[PDB]
Image (cartoon, rainbow, N blue to C red):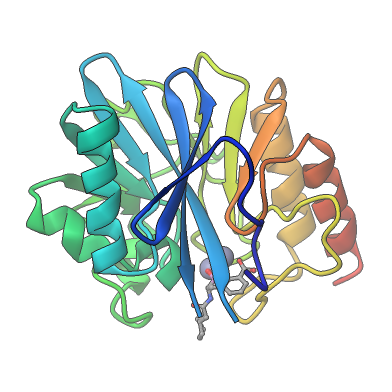
Length: 234
Ligand SMILES: [Zn+2]
Ligand SMILES: [Zn+2]
């Protein structure tokens, strides 16, 4: 890929997607769109069900995520949560709905989805003033702990911690510590980006593996480095 990590030992190719185990019950899914840009999301095994964070870029790619789950985990997918209304995170909604999978997004992501050319999720998350999801709107999310950090990469971007692990997912908000820019800022809130990145760090203070949309997993320095680049936008 031109944007995105390269394939590495421990990675499994399945169709045109790549899967990597990060923990006993957690995998990263990676899909590509043309050069090629990689996009990452997560798959979590929770008891007798599977939870998905983010679609792939397309419906066909997202169907392949479901196929890989069937082969390698062989448990039903109970729900998916998508972290904002752009193609890399929500482009494959139709595959989930075709399969009868309950889908969740920030209410604002669902409201923006038609303007962004995305299919809205079936259910909407809302958030307290401190950024934590209102639990009534996140039914049976199990280990997925959803946090809205504030506007940054987009106004609707949300983040997800995996309870019982050292993993937190920053989506497109967080860039890795070797990044030379903040990526695609076309819909970004440059005034609040830096504070939102720091808020993500403070919401998951013990996470040591930070998973991101367009880089391999990094340490907590990714959060600080992102916030310090965002400081220069103001
Ligand atoms: Zn985006
Ligand atoms: Zn992105």
